[PDB]
Image: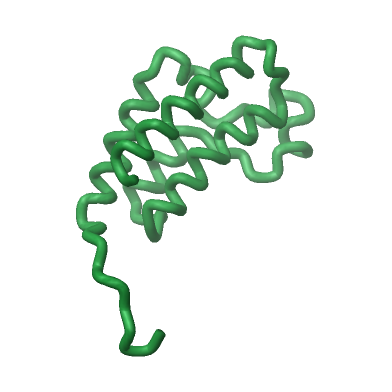
Length: 115
């Protein structure tokens, strides 16, 4: 509360560390469905159904331009990428499996880097 604060967690490396995680997600072999925004002119139903499209290139641009206020807003966009994927793709599809694999990969890096 006013003049009463928990000890200051060092967040000075968060930007660099989120960048490194995102590099590792970008270079994973199952990243291909997530590298670029879904083409809303060419994928029937996507625009209406997926209210907040997100992809790795959009996260990279947001990260590089200071549009994440803190490391949690960064994790929320990464998770959005996989939540969107689950919303639109059957579990038993290449893209559906890709999304589950990448979410697992992300969550482990996230825990090991920050928890």
